[PDB]
Length: 381
Image (cartoon, rainbow, N blue to C red; front, side, top):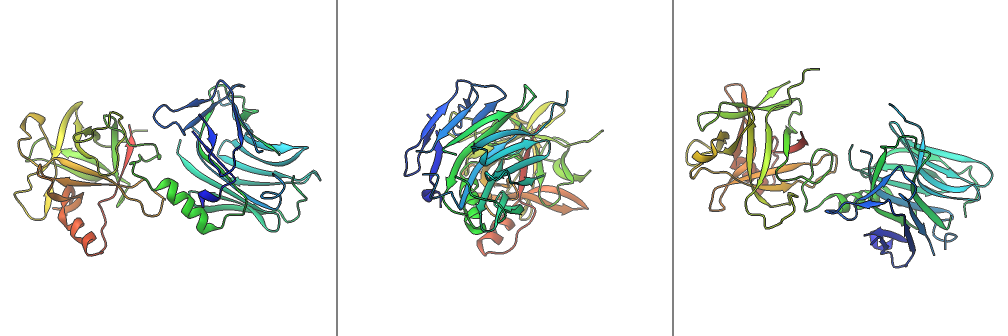
């Protein structure tokens, strides 16, 4: 559905839609150096992008849609405009406030319809049909809608990306992959749009940021997000486990270490082979097991790095791209010859949920049978 866009803003910034179209960038716009399509808009004039569509009437008179990713990273809160396409007091805009993302249509008869959604990357899609409603979707899912059949006609030639009326000097927004469409997208097309752009060869943290090497994370097991990971002693005779939960223990910190990646950047990619380090009392240890002993469930331990020997420690990182409610990760432990030991999960032994690598998970997947407990999220420390 992206190939049918009437504007596709992509990093220079350029419109890649079948139609050319003019971009003006002010001096104070920033692009992430690692992900150039990651646009940073600050609370400054010069921190503006102006898009001149070059025909408004046709395509978007009666029905049209917009999509983009956003992150919003003394209390000085108030409604401010972030994307503006109003002229002769009619058109549309996106606006932000505390706990609010706001869509506003205006129609020349001074009539206005407002739709609202109440530190995370979120995928927004807004659809419009003068015959029916304005609709807000978040991560491919309908959150709110308002009838707009009572509104009049809507002819702007110009879209302005700029914080307007924001009174906090530190406020900034992140946008990426802005598109305009000449039709009212349906729920299936929006899911497919989200799923395409979301489901990727890059692992994500809990907030949807790129997962990184050499960065401390807390590990969340999606079987029970109320449990934190703890260590029962360092060494092969100890183990890691899950235990039930201001004064809030978040558990043991994990660090993902490069092993086989030839990438100089520090983003964890799908199928990267890595080591996992565990921090215990401000010292690093290696996640590992002895796959030559025991049953299928290989209990994971925190090893002294100098004493790892030939223990199994190589982890294949995987993004799990199902329904996009969560930034799910899996970890397949391997020996030093590329043989699968098993996905990392947990097993209840003596009423403790001990971390394990188990080929049971891999065997279930092989025969299309249910797994649980082998899905993780990484929360930056």
